Image 1 (tube, rainbow over the protein chains, first blue to last red):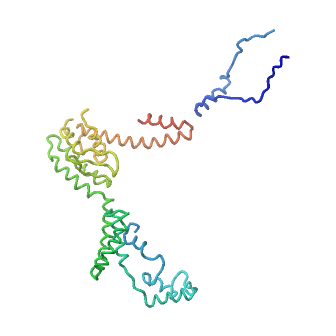
Image 2: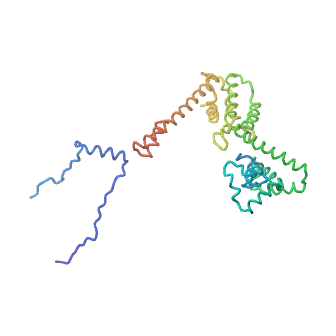
Image 3: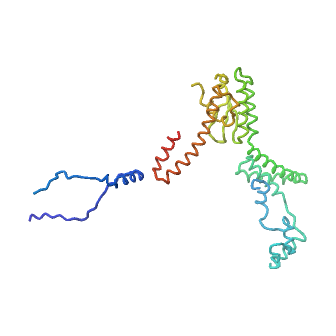
Length: 50
Length: 288
């Protein structure tokens, strides 16, 4: 009601890459595709919220 | 023939075609059609080209060899470094002016003797370059006159070392010895590094031939250069100079097989896929 407005011109996605060596980043790739090396995470709040 | 001062003078004064004076037989084989390849190539010329070659054949034209005899001399002076290549036109007009003031039957014969003399002197210098011995043997034997021929201890090691010292300057045509003030030196190549000091090395090795932290690093540079020209029986086994000459022969042989090992490891580290910065540093730290 108070006349505030937001308008999106453009959105760009950025992604910073560690310049890892191509034998090191291929060893790390091959280790992290094994199902025992799955990256498991956790919500910090960890709650169902009612 | 590319370094022949009269072949080079023929490529700068004589025509590149078949005139009937320098090449009389080769043009009479073509006028008279007795050539193997294309005999009938002379009948297919106009009368201006065909009759003007017959007239130069049945009565040929005389010529001056004087500009060709002098240019063979100038192109040998410029080749044996007697003149500069910029002075090649200056001394050519200077010699043509002298053989024009003093022209005779004696001088034109004497220029004919001297263009055979400079063919030899160009080839004699180029043989002496590839042999590479005459400037070094007269200055290494001049060095060894200064050094005494009788050390107190270890004369057997000393007279085989100085005989192997004559073997470097003989079996390496680029190596040379000279003098610069008091001392004499030894370069392993023309305009190259590893210059040892002979007068400082033999005043260091004198007193170490029978000893069985104390060596100047140019003496050790001399013991590195003399190592492939020294047998196991040329010096002793227990003597500290003889113990190092075997140790420097193993160091050359290990650096000769670490050279071939380097060319193998870096070849299979590019195809396997590594950092090209770290493939070249981890290999040397494995080899050094």
